[PDB]
Image: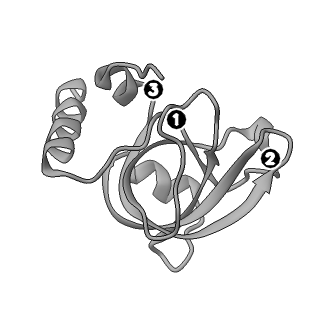
Amino acid sequence: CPERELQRREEEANVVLTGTVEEIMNVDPVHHTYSCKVRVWRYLKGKDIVTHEILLDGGNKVVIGGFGDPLICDNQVSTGDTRIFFVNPAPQYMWPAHRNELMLNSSLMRITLRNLEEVEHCVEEHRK
């Protein structure tokens, strides 16, 4: 499965965060996708966006849908998994199915210093 260059992935994602998958949510029969409740650790990008467009659960939990999407290479998660999430707020025309949800935009990434550093780097450059 081919994935896009990290630079384009950072581009097509207004929000990049890190967190833990606490629970698997319901399935989306229409798109053959599922959602999960995630406990956010830190935002690598788009924190302001999530603050003004998402109603948070317990102030540190978000729901991310889009898991299982065939077009995304690394797209599976289990309870307890920790990853870097490249996401976008759920668009209007996807309500109320995915209202108040972040949708996976690209492949999940493992938590390692290399990854954290590389992503911050691209978030840093592009931000100029």
Which residue is at a point 38% across and 62% down the rendered structure image? 19
Q: Which residue is drawn at 24% across and 25% down?
A: 126
Q: Are marks 2 and 3 in contact (CB under 8 Å)?
A: no
Q: Quadrant of the C terminus?
A: top left
Q: Which colour scheme is used?
A: one colour
Which residue position is annotated with label 1?
105
Of the image marks 1 and 2, the number of the one nearer the N terminus: 2
- Secondary element at image label 1: loop
Q: Earlier in the sequence, mark 1 or mark 3?
A: 3
Q: Where is residue 1 in the image (x, y as percent from the top left)?
A: 48, 23
- Return the disc, 2 or 3, that comes first in the chain's sequence: 3
**Label 2 environment density (alpha carbons within 10 Å; few <14, some 14–19, many ≥20):** few
Residue pictured at 68% horizontal, 38% vertical: 91
Foreground: disc 1 or disc 2:
1
Position of 22 relative to 92 (above/below): below
Mark 1 near mark 3, Cβ–Cβ under 8 Å?
yes
- Judged from this view, the residue extending furthest toward the right is 30
Q: Which amino acid does label 1 sit on?
A: Asn
> Whole-percent x and y of residue 69?
64, 36
Pointer 2: what residue? 95
Horizontal side of 19 relative to 96 (left or right) equals left
At label 3, the amino acid type is Glu
Q: What element carries label 2?
A: loop
Residue 47 percent location from the top left of the image: 38, 53
**Is residue 60 positioned above or below 27 on the image?**
below
Q: Which of marks 1 and 3 is in front?
A: 1
**Does 32 appear above or below 20?**
above
Residue shown at 14% from the left, 43% from the top: 114
